[PDB]
Amino acid sequence: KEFQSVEEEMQSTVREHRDGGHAGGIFNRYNILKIQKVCNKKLWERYTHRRKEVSEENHNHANERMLFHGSPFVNAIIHKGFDERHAYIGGMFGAGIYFAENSSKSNQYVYGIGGGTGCPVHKDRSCYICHRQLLFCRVTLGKSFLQFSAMKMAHSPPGHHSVTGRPSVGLALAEYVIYRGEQAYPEYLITYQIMRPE
Ligand SMILES: NC(=O)c1cccc(N)c1
Ligand SMILES: [Zn+2]
Image 1 (cartoon, rainbow, N blue to C red):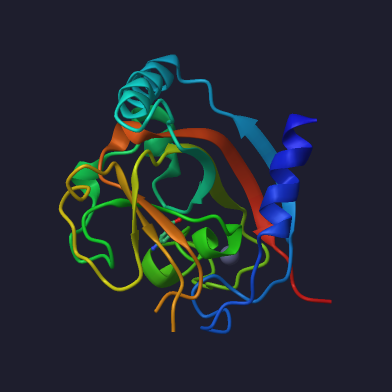
Image 2 (cartoon, rainbow, N blue to C red):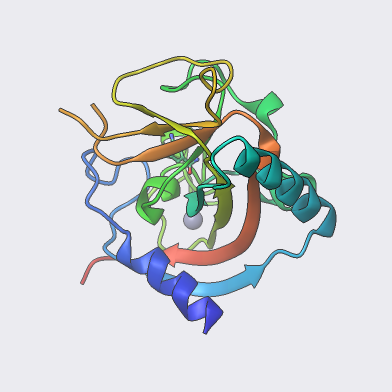
């Protein structure tokens, strides 16, 4: 089924992080509690209209990918959509909206940048009790600019529609950055817990 494929993607993309679980917590797998498909017709039209535009500018190819997004503002994103106006220029690839192909990378951003102070009730970044929320998004990358080192962009590079952060000696894992909110749709809302290693 549809939700089994989302759970498998969530579980199989977990990696061992270099910070030893400082930001996201210590875990090898999750306890998937709920997977909800977000049905926001106004946001979907905004996304498909921009997707068609990008396809025409990238040899009839949208370069669409299913990627994870961690944020304490998931409730605002599912109702209002992604918003580049809230993006900070101080990020590695500048004022963009960041996505990961590894669920455990996006899990480090659920309670804030670098996990913030953790869950709101126990102030624990490795909290195994509090229910976390992650987004599994449809992202239009189009002509993606391949980059290894820090490149503080305000917008996509000329002639491009996104930035792909590739790992080097550098990033540990890949990341995908868009500079227009309408180039991503929050398709699935995942309610989960990080699980204590066995
Ligand atoms: N907010 C996120 O899920 C995310 C994804 C990739 C890279 C970064 N920095 C954040
Ligand atoms: Zn907690």
